[PDB]
Image (cartoon, rainbow, N blue to C red; front, side):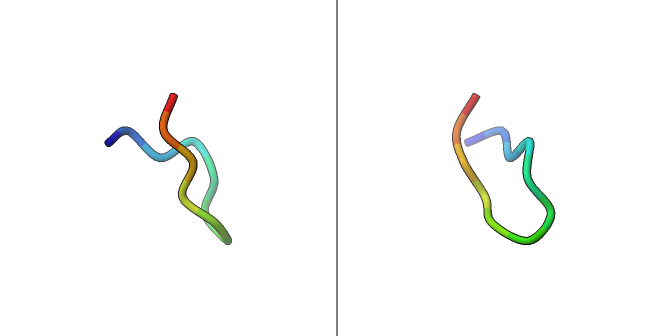
Length: 12
């Protein structure tokens, strides 16, 4: 999944 967060990966 594409992570937009560095501290926490959230699928965009």
